[PDB]
Image (tube, rainbow, N blue to C red):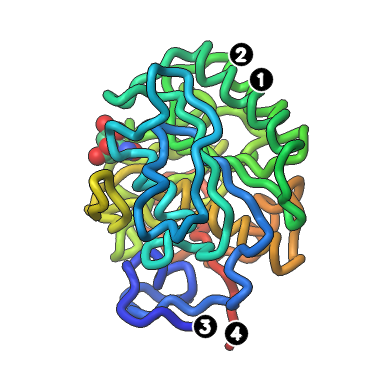
Amino acid sequence: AAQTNAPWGLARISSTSPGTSTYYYDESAGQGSCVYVIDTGIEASHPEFEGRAQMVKTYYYSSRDGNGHGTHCAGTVGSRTYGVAKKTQLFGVKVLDDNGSGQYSTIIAGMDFVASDKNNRNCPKGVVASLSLGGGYSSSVNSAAARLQSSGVMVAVAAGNNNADARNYSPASEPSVCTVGASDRYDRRSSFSNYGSVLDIFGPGTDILSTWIGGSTRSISGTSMATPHVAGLAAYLMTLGKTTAASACRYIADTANKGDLSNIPFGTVNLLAYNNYQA
Ligand SMILES: NC(=O)CN(CC(=O)O)CC(=O)O
Ligand SMILES: [Ca+2]
């Protein structure tokens, strides 16, 4: 399949060079996979989600995305126009409030929730969890992300936006999950992207068009926007049978575009998420 005039990030994950405009992907599109977006929520009524989105859990007085961040991230995963995996099932877990904050205790409870809840859902191609959140180093936060991954979910987490080594942030610094840095449409490391040996992979993270609350759309930037590209890619590859939850981060790094990014520090991987799709 081909999406003409796609958001640059989508075009970028289907090309070996920057600057293209069509997103080419296999039509299976993540069908039969499931991606838990653990964030401020998902506006599942947005027409872009085509009924494929639902809230399954909130830790606040409402399950509504009053912020927009989780709806944006969910749209990069699996919206019809802005998503990598256009036929994936999306589940919202609201661990962040409408200002975008959440206590680590809440975030950890959300991760243990998903490890259990996936057992009450039909996800025959497998389960991914996208975590565009984090704060300072926490061994308990890292532990929770490791359990989620060990339970059989492909965990993708934001490297963070501190232009610093991700070793000092969580869940970015948990080695067993997939830690995602951000790039821009000229193949530079994004100005704010964290870096470090613990990064697994980069995805598109500067100026990313996606869904927004109130049935709308907007462009925003962050390792939060790169993470759902990687989460969607894993869903897509899992549906295609080319990888499993346990091995997907490795597979994506194995098959990445290599050495394309500029301003990558010594000791950080120069790998950009790539779907190797051949019409
Ligand atoms: N979402 C991100 O990675 C960074 N951004 C994105 C945004 O929310 O507009 C700022 C923030 O989170 O404060
Ligand atoms: Ca890792």
Q: Classify mark 2: residues with Cα within 10 Å, few (<14), some (14-19) or many (20+).
A: some
| First along the sequence among labels 3 and 2 | 3
Q: Quadrant of residue 125?
A: bottom right
Mark number for residue 140?
2
**Residue 12 appears in the picture as rendered:** yes
Left or right: 134, with 98 as reference point: right
Secondary structure of residue under mark 2: helix
- The x and y percentages for residue 98 are 30, 25
- The x and y percentages for residue 277 are 58, 78
Left or right: 142, with 77 as reference point: right
Question: Residues at badges 3 and 4 in contact (C-beta under 8 Å)?
Answer: no
- The x and y percentages for residue 135 are 42, 21
Report the amino acid beneath label 4.
Gln
Residue hosting label 4 = 278
The span from disc 4 to disc 1 (Cα, nearest Å) is 38 Å
Mark number for residue 143?
1
Residue in the foreground of this view, choosing between 183 and 105: 105
Residue occupying the point 49% across, 79% down: 24
- The x and y percentages for residue 34 are 63, 50
| First along the sequence among labels 3 and 4 | 3
Residue in the foreground of this view, choosing between 102 and 255: 102
The span from disc 3 to disc 4 (Cα, nearest Å) is 10 Å
Report the amino acid beneath label 3.
Ala
The correct choice, above or below, for 145 with respect to 238 in the image is: above
Mark number for residue 1?
3
Report the amino acid beneath label 1.
Ser
Report the amino acid beneath label 2.
Ser
Question: Residues at badges 2 and 1 in contact (C-beta under 8 Å)?
Answer: yes
Which is closer to the viewer, label 1 or label 3?
A: 3
Secondary structure of residue under mark 3: loop
Residue occupying the point 41% across, 55% down: 76
The span from disc 3 to disc 2 (Cα, nearest Å) is 42 Å
